[PDB]
Image: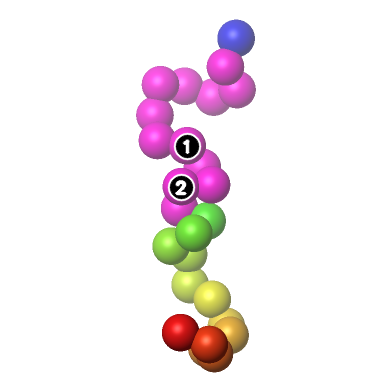
Amino acid sequence: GVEGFNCYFPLQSYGFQPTNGVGYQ
């Protein structure tokens, strides 16, 4: 019933994904 399988959520990586905007640390 849960979209996908028993594994770490997708968004979990979206927060660590490589960004192209370095500013305001």
As helix, strand or loop, the secondary structure at mark 2 comes to helix
Residue at screen point 47% across, 37% down: 9
| Range covered by the magenta-colored residues | 2-13
Name the residue furthest left: 7
Q: Amino acid at mark 2?
A: Gln
* Circle 1 crowding by C-alpha within 10 Å: few under 14, some 14–19, many from 20: few
Q: Amino acid at mark 1?
A: Phe
Give the camera-side residue of 25 and 15.
25
Name the residue furthest top: 1
Name the residue furthest front: 24
| Residue 4, horizontal then vertical, whole percent | 54, 24
Please, what is the dominant secondary structure of the magenta stretch? loop
| Residue 3, horizontal then vertical, whole percent | 60, 22
Q: CA distance from mark 1 to mark 2?
A: 5 Å
Residue beneath label 2, please? 12
| Residue 11, horizontal then vertical, whole percent | 53, 47
Residue at screen point 52% across, 56% down: 14
In the rendered image, which quarter is residue 20 located in? bottom right
Residue 21: mark in rendering: none
On screen, residue 8 versus residue 3, left or right, reads left
Residue at screen point 51% across, 42% down: 10
Residue at screen point 58% across, 85% down: 21
Residue beneath label 1, please? 9
* Circle 2 crowding by C-alpha within 10 Å: few under 14, some 14–19, many from 20: few
